[PDB]
Length: 147
Length: 49
Length: 49
Image 1 (cartoon, one colour):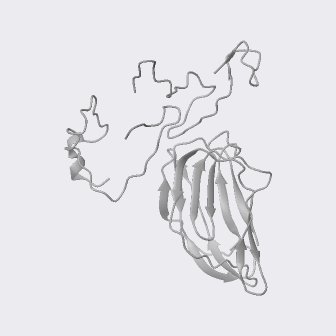
Image 2 (tube, chains in turn brown, red, purple):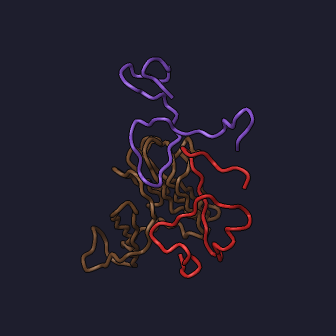
Image 3 (cartoon, helix red, strand yellow):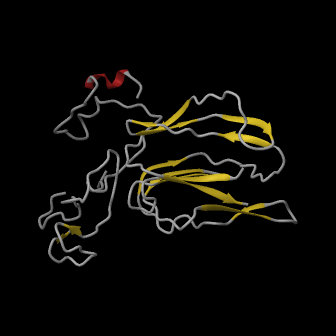
């Protein structure tokens, strides 16, 4: 459970259309919005000893937010918030085609089992959902979490 | 409602999970231009968008 | 929305340095470089809003 956030956009400093997607521990916060960023994007959680409590602290993603063009505020739920070491277990693969403006999202998620670099075998990338945006896209970056 | 937003910053709203109709576009206000592109406009009560 | 002194609460963008994409919003109000003499927020010549 390491990669939590993402940003999809041309200039990614609130000058061209620059999304923020974060699959955070509770809510889906997907924001096609005007966003101003620091150097290298991260997320943040912190873990204690007396109880096994993962606490959410860090916010250095945006300094400024007023505008939004496509907001997506979904159900809250519990995230298991792992850091567990051992064999590789989780592929959450997000293949992106954008034909005729509408940025598309697939889904394929599997409890795999091996040690290291990507396993072989067939895995379909079948359609899931389509965010029907129409915007200027040139680059994108990813926001990792810091456990 | 009382006030929309301007044209450089247009206003956005999400609509789902409700029943609509165009036959009630005749009472609260008289509309000056009512055109639908790409679909037969008096068939709005006949589909699911 | 028609006041006796005028309704000056709604704005249209007069000019923009580039063109648009569909389903997009920008509210950046930087000084419009019409020609030479780049503005950086001075409103001189070739510097419009």
